[PDB]
Amino acid sequence: SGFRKMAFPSGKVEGCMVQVICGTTTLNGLWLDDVVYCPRAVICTSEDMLNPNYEDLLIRKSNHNFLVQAGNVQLRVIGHSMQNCVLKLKVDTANPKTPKYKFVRIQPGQTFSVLACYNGSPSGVYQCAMRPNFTIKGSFLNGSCGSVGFNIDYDCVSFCYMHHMELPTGVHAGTDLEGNFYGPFVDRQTAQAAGTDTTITVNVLAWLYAAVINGDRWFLNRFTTTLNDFNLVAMKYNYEPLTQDHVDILGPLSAQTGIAVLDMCASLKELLQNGMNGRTILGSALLEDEFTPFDVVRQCSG
Amino acid sequence: SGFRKMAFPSGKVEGCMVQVICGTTTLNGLWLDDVVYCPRAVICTSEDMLNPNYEDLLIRKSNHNFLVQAGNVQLRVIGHSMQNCVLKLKVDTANPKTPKYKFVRIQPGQTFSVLACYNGSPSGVYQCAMRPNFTIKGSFLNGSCGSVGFNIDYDCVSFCYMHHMELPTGVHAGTDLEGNFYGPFVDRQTAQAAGTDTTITVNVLAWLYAAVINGDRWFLNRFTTTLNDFNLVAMKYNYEPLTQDHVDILGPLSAQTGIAVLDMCASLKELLQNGMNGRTILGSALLEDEFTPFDVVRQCSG
Amino acid sequence: TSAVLQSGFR
Amino acid sequence: TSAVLQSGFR
Image (cartoon, rainbow over all chains, first blue to last red; front, side, top):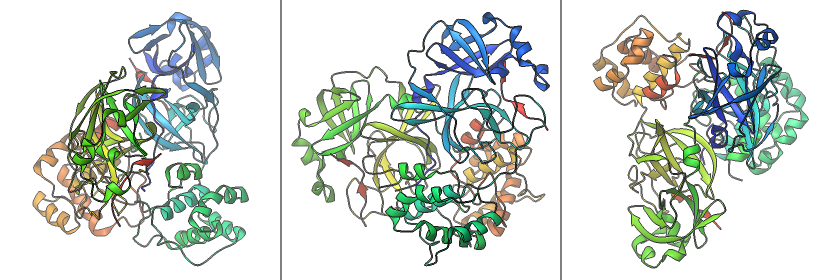
């Protein structure tokens, strides 16, 4: 029993983290085989950052301008190239700790584990969801740029996020490992704001099933609703529409608990319209939307 | 910016996890140097578990009754002994991945990272606090027994918890790595219940300072209070008394924010007496008590 | 209800 | 306020 925000074990990724220094700018890189991937922001100085022309900045660099340190071992850079908002630094040594890996791009509503790092050294691990507005609510300080997000499946690490920046609201933005930003953001120190965000309805329902599996049942009712009538309510509360595919994905949790998906929707409708009236669900006084159906199944009894 | 429940990177501990099998009972062990530490519950069968006499059960075992697997390598057990509620299985091979480590026992109110494991294989990592009643609110399924909790300081792993059991309320109980239970619990399948729990006041105050550092200030007031008058209020709400040492430990956070500790106490008094009136603090609609002052400093800007 | 020693069966 | 590229200084 129990339900916690749980990250994947980080060791496979820890063995891949390095420090990249260009001039006085330092950040983290990801060393897989004979390539180190890092944010192209490493080539900017403080003043370059308002309006950097990265192609210009890069053509003025050579391999020797990049110092890559893996623990107490300096790696010699023997080539460099830019791919979108990441740099690929070819090094003379293949990382002996490279795990099986993929570069995947995730969807809004999906979760992943973040290994926060500073100076190439891992400092903490936590779970994040990609919000509907393509930001993440992380915990990152200066020096964290280049920290990565990932999921693990059967010892294959699927890297999905590289951290770049913090927006004025305190949320975070970054790229996939091909260097393409999630969302309408750019790697420069300008006023940028995310679109209005929405609540991930299917994940709230998944977490309500986790709660039932864990013995929290007070929010259940003998009522039901239609999908159409539910979405009419969800729209008023700034929840994403719930699709038939979402209903299907919740099938296994519905089967395990005996609570039809549309019945749980009726419970959520009542929670939205009434609030919690002083009670908690799985230790929270708010409706939690950062657990996917997979996260619930992975963690909850069968 | 940002504030998240963050675990320590788990790689150093992942390299120490093994599977221990005795008969049809399987659980996790911790392999450091040439010793594997595991819960003595590995020697019980289903029926032994209501009233096991562990000294009897153990004298009826020999080294060959313990099968220890570290990945695809079987480790030969060459000695065994019981220390309190843990077994020490001497193996013929020193773990080449042993980190610098200590066995520490923690206090109620302190946090640590849990590496949940099944069949010797790490599955997830999350943070826990040791509650005042010596339970932890974890996430553990059958097969998790022997998973460990730890903190890291300068590449030294301080192991503080080994998981044993789940209580009827769904909370968790275990031992230090010397095999001594936290709290008035025993390794047998009997009715056991924890004492009434209380809220960790110093940690709530630390989290309110994290909130201020992160720009949540709505709960501040121009009021102040005395320590004595604050504790009169805290007692009514089932909060632990706040000591002068707690005040001292909060010194650095008070200095960083310019908010005197007793002023933050006045804010907490008002939050206890009034509730939140629909607002959130650091993404929570409840007062969070599972972040220590260290956790806040470690994670928050300086 | 009793406490459960959360070992696994194999 | 502007976005911040969270590199470090050294």
